[PDB]
Amino acid sequence: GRLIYTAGGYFRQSLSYLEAYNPSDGTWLRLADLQVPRSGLAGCVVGGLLYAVGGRNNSPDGNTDSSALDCYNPMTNQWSPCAPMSVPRNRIGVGVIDGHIYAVGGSHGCIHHNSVERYEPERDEWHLVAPMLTRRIGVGVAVLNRLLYAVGGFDGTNRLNSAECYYPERNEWRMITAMNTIRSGAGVCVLHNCIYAAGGYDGQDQLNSVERYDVATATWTFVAPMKHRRSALGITVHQGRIYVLGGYDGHTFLDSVECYDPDTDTWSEVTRMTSGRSGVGVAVTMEPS
């Protein structure tokens, strides 16, 4: 039994919520709050543990970007801090290769990062690796065949349709074919052996289009678009299907959750979150005990 976990996010302030959706019985389980409210974070899973990486605390007190790494154990319903990153990374992207967490890009105040670093859970250590060719805030990140892809984002001045690929063995980034559409804060994931980039923001419109990258042909192809335009959505994959959570449509912080069926190239709304938010971290792991 795997659930879809959503951590943090933003609605009027940064949020502490951890909630887990059960796509079979439809419920949302309310779980242990994050230690610190965070929006603009990313989520991932290594060895069954849920990790919340980076982000930013927008509170009535003040606003602070976050270098924090925190670990949630479904067996105990408890969060535990980890070693933090070398720098705060708001609107971070993250990917998992060989049991290590890669932290990609993001911002710290007016610094737009091109740096990247790698966490090793077995030693609770971060180490910087080769920086990207591009500064990317709101970057989407996905892992295909043990290669790390950084897709889209915002360089501080321009929103981006470029994508690059990191080779861990080589510690090098290499540009790949650009997307058709400019997207910052899109949801990016790997479904079968394709990288999907859904939604986002191009500096004028929040987007509902979705495109898919095939490594064999090295090109991006549009698939069916989402029902709702959304930037800063959360995305994950559960049992062969893509789920997108919340986001911001230019007027509203969405509670809509949509589900993509690749076999039918169709999106459908499947649930509503308990309250609308953007900038959540999302990942899938076993239900709690």
Image (spheres, helix red, strand yellow):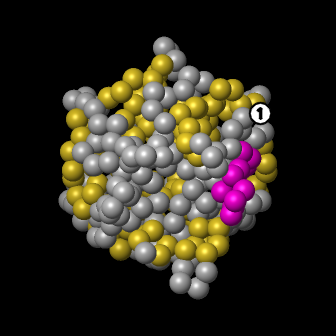
Residue reaching furthest top?
217
Q: Identify the magenta region.
A: 107-120
How many numbered circles does the render carry?
A: 1
Q: To which quarter of the image does residue 129 belong?
A: top right
Q: At 61% from the left edge and 80% from the top edge, which residue is drawn? A: 62
- Residue 219 rendering spot, x and y as whole percentages: 48, 19
Residue 73, magenta (yes or no): no
Question: Is residue 264 toward the left or the right of residue 203 in the image?
Answer: left
In depth, the one of 156 and 130 nearer the eye is: 156
Q: Decide if residue 245 is in sight here.
A: no
Disc 1 secondary structure class: loop
Residue 111, magenta (yes or no): yes
Q: Decide if residue 39 is in sight here.
A: yes
Q: At 24% from the left edge and 62% from the top edge, which residue is drawn? A: 272
The residue singled out by tag 1 in the image is: 171
Circle 1: is it few (<14), some (14-19), or many (20+) Cα within 10 Å? few
In depth, the one of 216 and 72 nearer the eye is: 216
- Residue 173 rendering spot, x and y as whole percentages: 71, 31
The amino acid beneath tag 1 is: Asn
Question: Is residue 19 toward the left or the right of residue 143 in the image?
Answer: left
